[PDB]
Amino acid sequence: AQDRETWGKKIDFLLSVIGFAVDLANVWRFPYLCYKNGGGAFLVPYLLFMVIAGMPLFYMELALGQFNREGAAGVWKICPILKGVGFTVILISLYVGFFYNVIIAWALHYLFSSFTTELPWIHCNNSWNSPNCSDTTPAAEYFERGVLHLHQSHGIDDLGPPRWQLTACLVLVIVLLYFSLWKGVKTSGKVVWITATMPYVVLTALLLRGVTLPGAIDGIRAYLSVDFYRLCEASVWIDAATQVCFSLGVGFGVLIAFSSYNKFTNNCYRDAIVTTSINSLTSFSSGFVVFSFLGYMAQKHSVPIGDVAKDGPGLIFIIYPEAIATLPLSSAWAVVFFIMLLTLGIDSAMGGMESVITGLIDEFQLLHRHRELFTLFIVLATFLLSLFCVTNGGIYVFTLLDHFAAGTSILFGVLIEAIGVAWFYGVGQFSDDIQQMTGQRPSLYWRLCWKLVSPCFLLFVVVVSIVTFRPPHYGAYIFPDWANALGWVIATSSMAMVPIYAAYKFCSLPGSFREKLAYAIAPEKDRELVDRGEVRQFTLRHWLKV
Ligand SMILES: CC(C)CCC[C@@H](C)[C@H]1CC[C@H]2[C@@H]3CC=C4C[C@@H](OC(=O)CCC(=O)O)CC[C@]4(C)[C@H]3CC[C@]12C
Ligand SMILES: CC(C)CCC[C@@H](C)[C@H]1CC[C@H]2[C@@H]3CC=C4C[C@@H](O)CC[C@]4(C)[C@H]3CC[C@]12C
Ligand SMILES: CC(C)CCC[C@@H](C)[C@H]1CC[C@H]2[C@@H]3CC=C4C[C@@H](O)CC[C@]4(C)[C@H]3CC[C@]12C
Ligand SMILES: CC(C)CCC[C@@H](C)[C@H]1CC[C@H]2[C@@H]3CC=C4C[C@@H](O)CC[C@]4(C)[C@H]3CC[C@]12C
Ligand SMILES: COC(=O)[C@H]1[C@@H](OC(=O)c2ccccc2)C[C@@H]2CC[C@H]1N2C
Ligand SMILES: [Cl-]
Ligand code: NA
């Protein structure tokens, strides 16, 4: 049995986790959400849900991965019946790889288009521009008709052939991903030294550029404006809970995979605290750049900052490029901005594909000795299934996947994972494992958060996400009913692995229905006890313990 590889340095693991957590959305979505829900007031619920349910779940995932020394699927030897959860998260990661890499392809396309003295999104005396342009705006028109070519597609049912420019950019992104992941963590941990730190350098450059622009200080003030009376709204609290759930990186199996390569005696508690703090602070600080630029644009157009900020995939390819085109040395700033976008997306894509590859390789030993070939297969499958999003109507497929690929699926996966780790396995045994690893047993606060607060919070978020579901849309396009049905099928194909694997495991285990249950819910480490008839999970005391 080949010894499992470990991170060459700890800075490798920390930067991998930070690069995965810090992505395009986290840098450009969170501050906009904060502004839209009371600005600084939105930090009250967010932090709260970070203290009681976010940090505990991050810590749980890291500790579980580190102790069990396996990926998302192999980690579930603590409760075999729930092992499908692993596959669920893996599937989600795989699904997110079929559309997320197209964002990096768009960023690469804009980067190659930025090496010119005349940026192609400053005016609309171009072949791709409709007569209606009047400074839809030139930047939005360029994005939609010169890069995506949406005007040539009538909807998700009229995708058309893949675009060769976008296909070439996707090929470049895919090659980068493969050569970043083919050798394991020994190369990924060194690639994150560049892809996880360049975004901060470019963000500092853009922050120093923006604050000096006219009208940027007004945008910053609007960002930091505190409206506590907005906290009486349930929408603010629901948005905070949803943002905490979807901004941490839990539910994809990536934290488990990353921590599975950590030394057993590593301190996952400090790692969780540090990484969560860095991710949250990065998301908060990116708001200063976002809203300096938004306030500058608002002053230029003489409109409220709320009107400038659009919502959608092209929020980073329409508004910020438009602001950059108006700066001195606009070409250099555009190149820097799109390099930052590439480095923000590439590390997250690497983290997701690492989750997929680690989980599947750990599950099946046939792929253990061949990681290069399996990485090539996974990457080529991602590329081939990513070709639907680079078609003429590729924004519609991208929107469908972005809405349904990791929505309620992530929340359900994290909920079932928390239940399995805190109830089926027990917070007592999890705490004993953490004490064995780090030497310090989790305090009562962590145990209570894992056992009671986190499951209730995740169940509430799942329920509100299902109840307040709104079908996806792009611009004036209304997705057809069959498109919504296909999206729900995609969302449920991840989550159905839990019941499917539960049924398969229950039927596979030999014995009566009391032997099957005992061997399915009891940890594999307790096998001897289960043989004598000493199942902890069969005692009410186990379930009521904290
Ligand atoms: C969005 C902007 C304002 C950035 C601020 C966010 C982070 C800096 C916050 C979000 C969640 C917070 C954490 C939530 C929970 C805890 C556990 C807490 O520990 C305890 O409650 C005691 C238990 C024990 O010591 O065993 C120590 C602070 C810490 C790490 C918090 C540190 C600060 C964090 C990372
Ligand atoms: C395992 C699977 C479900 C994960 C997601 C893969 C993606 C890339 C797949 C799954 C279902 C696919 C869609 C199935 C139906 C159609 C209608 C057809 O007229 C054009 C292609 C289009 C719009 C496909 C686009 C790509 C698609 C969204
Ligand atoms: C011009 C400046 C801002 C660019 C540099 C910013 C980058 C390199 C900085 C910003 C935040 C930093 C991280 C913050 C704290 C830690 C925890 C420590 O235990 C290991 C290093 C690590 C993980 C840092 C690595 C470098 C880092 C990612
Ligand atoms: C539409 C595409 C992208 C979906 C890919 C799904 C993944 C999870 C599938 C595709 C091929 C599969 C492998 C095919 C061959 C074997 C050998 C056999 O002993 C079962 C396990 C194993 C190793 C499978 C594991 C799961 C696997 C890697
Ligand atoms: C698309 O989903 C994401 O963007 C997630 C994540 O991305 C992926 O999980 C992923 C998976 C496969 C391919 C590409 C990206 C990065 C950060 C952390 C959680 C969230 N994001 C804030
Ligand atoms: Cl966040
Ligand atoms: Na990232």
Image (cartoon, rainbow, N blue to C red):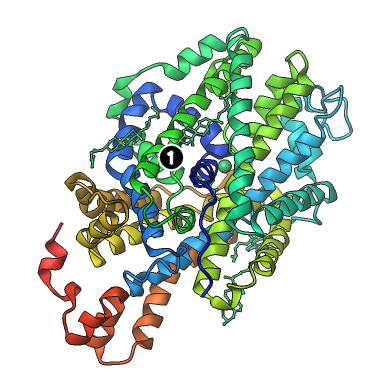
* Residue 365 in sight: yes
Residue type, label 1: Thr
| Residue positioned 54% across, 76% down in the render | 365
- Element type where label 1 sits in the image: helix
403 relative position to 545: left or right? right
Work out whether 49 lies above or below 77.
above
Snapshot quadrant of residue 264: bottom left
Residue wearing tag 1: 275
Residue 226 percent coordinates (x, y): 36, 18
Q: Quadrant of ligand 6?
A: top left
**Ligand 3 under 8 Å from disc 1 Cβ:** yes
| Residue positioned 72% across, 31% down in the render | 140
Closest to the observer, 156 or 164: 164
Assess disc 1: are there few (<14), some (14-19) or many (≥20) residues with their C-alpha within 10 Å of its C-alpha.
Answer: many
Residue 513 percent coordinates (x, y): 25, 88
Closest to the observer, 178 or 451: 178
Quadrant where the C terminus sits is bottom left
| Residue positioned 52% across, 15% down in the render | 219
